[PDB]
Image: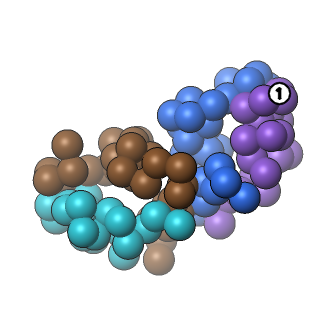
Chain colours: A purple, B blue, C brown, D cyan
């Protein structure tokens, strides 16, 4: 989930936008 | 600001700024 | 901190602190 | 929605928790 992709690994805009409504 | 390790309130902040008026969901357990 | 007008990042922050490990959803348009 | 209840009116814990997962 988001923690694995953006906190314990380096985040990206591509991944962040997967969590926008 | 998005191309780094972002945790906790720092991650929430990034979601808030990127998603804008769309809003977002923060699901740290899923 | 929750019994006031909370907007934007201030509202996100409150959701983050209250909801904890549950996470939350921020839907300003709905 | 949350903006009406917590931003343009005074928020409450009861209402905030409606938006926890």
Looking at the image, which residue is at 78% across and 56% down? A18
Image position of D16 (left or right of C26): left
Q: Which residue is mark 1?
A: A10
Label count reads 1
Q: Is residue B12 at all visible to an observer of this figure? A: yes
Chain letter of mark 1 equals A
**Does D14 sit above or below residue B27?**
below
Looking at the image, which residue is at 53% across and 50% down? C21
**Does B27 sit above or below residue C8?**
below
- x, y percentage for residue C28? 45, 65
Q: Residues within 10 Å of mark 1 (few under 14, many from 20)?
A: some
Looking at the image, which residue is at 47% across and 77% down? C30
Q: Quadrant of residue B5?
A: top right
- x, y percentage for residue A3? 73, 41
Image position of B11 (left or right of B9): right
**Does B17 sit above or below residue D21?**
above
- x, y percentage for residue B21? 53, 59
Callout 1: SS: loop
Looking at the image, which residue is at 60% across and 54% down? B26
Please state, as top left, top right, bottom left or bottom right, where the N terminus of chain D lies in the image: bottom left
- Residue closer to the observer: C11 or D15: D15
Q: Is residue B21 at all visible to an observer of this figure? A: no
């Amino acid at each position: 989930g988001i923690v694995e992709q953006c906190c314990t690994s380096i985040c990206s805009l591509y991944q962040l936008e997967n969590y926008c409504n | 600001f998005v191309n780094q390790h972002l945790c906790g309130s720092h991650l929430v902040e990034a979601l808030y700024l990127v998603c804008g008026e769309r809003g977002f969901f923060y699901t740290p357990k899923t």
